[PDB]
Image 1 (tube, helix red, strand yellow):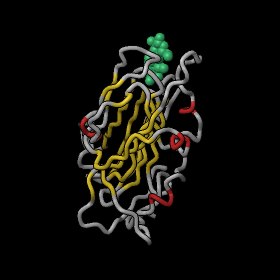
Image 2 (cartoon, rainbow, N blue to C red):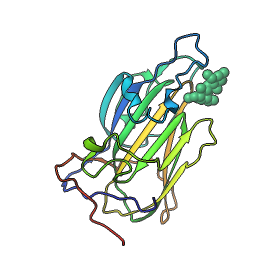
Image 3 (cartoon, helix red, strand yellow):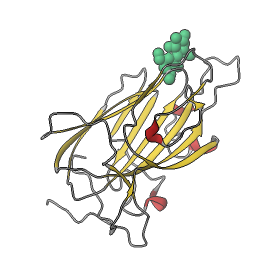
Image 4 (cartoon, helix red, strand yellow):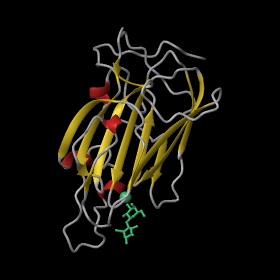
Length: 226
Ligand SMILES: OC[C@H]1O[C@@H](O[C@H]2[C@H](O)[C@@H](O)[C@H](O)O[C@@H]2CO)[C@H](O)[C@@H](O)[C@H]1O
Ligand SMILES: [Ca+2]
């Protein structure tokens, strides 16, 4: 979808950052082969399966550079460490093995083609646009109804759709859903943005990520090109 749908909330002062939910991703019982839980590859794990795991936290105002590489001291071992400051989550968690969901809206600074590139260890699935991620100012009621991933990356796969190239309007806020899993060992998440008019890739999304309350009527985008 080259021209994803955006949204036009009625809001004077939009809330900065995305929402985040963290969930457990336990290893299998010691002695299993392989050591890691394979659930993360199930088509419905990112839709409702993660809800069968333990909720670790719901966090707000996630903004900044969300990229990280975590080097596990050893494999098949649950080890504790911390996320980058952008995640607004300061306490140690099992960086070797966890599930993370981010959602909210992306606001472009300049109208035009935007290329988002992703890489992950182990898994990063991205939905982008109204409908595809969720409905405009109707997130809660459409939360589990996201469509085909606009980008996806899975460690060890002949993966692909490591990028998404879309025409965006600076006047709209675009629903975005980012689903991450580390099954074991090293963990890594990279999201970057390249615009056609700007020479430097963007890695700090401080000014681009927003959250909005849902409304009875919704807030469909008021920019259209056909
Ligand atoms: O290499 C990244 C990759 O590691 C897997 O773990 C491997 C590890 O690479 C290897 O040194 C060890 O001997 O076996 C491990 C298999 O349990 C992770 O499973 C994978 O998620 C990546 O992080
Ligand atoms: Ca891993």
